[PDB]
Length: 195
Ligand SMILES: [Zn+2]
Image (cartoon, rainbow, N blue to C red; front, side):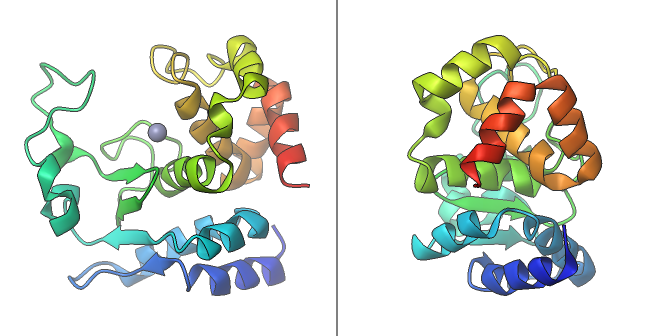
């Protein structure tokens, strides 16, 4: 990622990202925007075109008014864990909401990076017309969909494998190289999508 392109994408993200009212680590919110800025500018401009907002949160997801309906709701597969959506740090699809500070793997979620994974869902659904459900991607998923691990989740849901692969592709050079090695067809597919 070249520095001038990053700044251009951050400028675009200034028209996408919404910062919260409450108090939060401004430097960490900025770091999240910096990581999002590695996403290909064409996707970012398309999110902006669709008026998609990336809402950064200063607290729990379910303490946001528009997600309060998820209070106490147990996510699929989380039965018996004692955890609920109140414990989920982010979501992506038709909207994007992300708790500041919870980017890294293990911060209440299993993704390599929260904001890239969830924003990938929004790009998939809003920008790319659910390409993760396409026949082309389904063929790739059938072969490579377990190769980032979490086989009972990423390996089962092509939308999740897409989002995680997208996050590997764009997080940093290390994860990008790892994806190329582990999932070469997925890597080529993403490379060509951004052409
Ligand atoms: Zn996901």
